[PDB]
Image 1 (cartoon, one colour):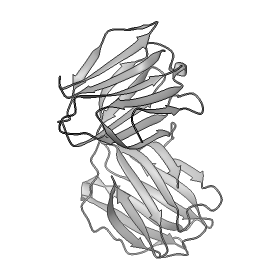
Image 2 (cartoon, helix red, strand yellow):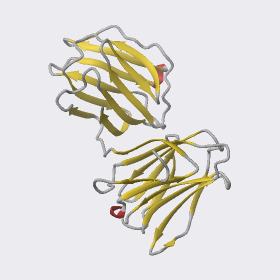
Image 3 (cartoon, one colour):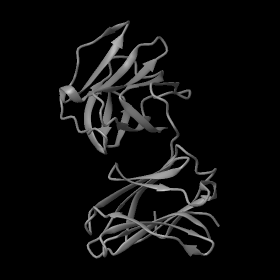
Image 4 (cartoon, helix red, strand yellow):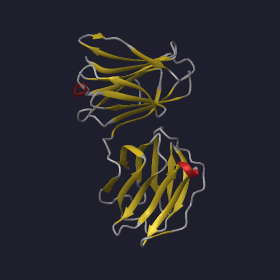
Length: 266
């Protein structure tokens, strides 16, 4: 990720899809920009300003910017930034550190977004775009090799602000559940378990629930040779020793009070 970083979308930026930019700032950093544009028009321009202590949202169109809209920059110079832009049919939804801080209504057609560019006083460390509107409860097959050792499932989700629990199931053909992952806010813990031949095993719930209602999170289930390695927001939250053959895990369920915005198999 050198800057200026420019990237080329393969298909339209569509409702349901999220663009994620993470990065590092310096102690002399002044401003960095994120633009969604074509090739000219900039349907969304984001200027994070440490000089003014604001984030500035705008649209460049017909050779000129329009009226600015502003929000408070929660970032002090130095320290990491996490900016996520989800396109909808009427607006972009922008979240800072996985908390929504701005709705920005379309001013020109979202379908003009063919590129994005990051620039300025930022050391970029992570970019990704994709996602869709994932209906919940969710249920899908997993590719072919499914989720096998050496592969990881990456789930982007947002626990509902007034929810009490939600669950992710990693399944095998017979309907066995190799890992049931069940954050429960009313017990301040995340239950992990397996469902073998219709019966649930013990219940590993050790650890501090790092999730927070209304705050997006990054969930990663790294299938390894002897255990799952479960990462939450970039740090290992638990390991779960395999109670079944960890090959042939080809099903995925998601239920409960959760909004899911991203699934990627890695």
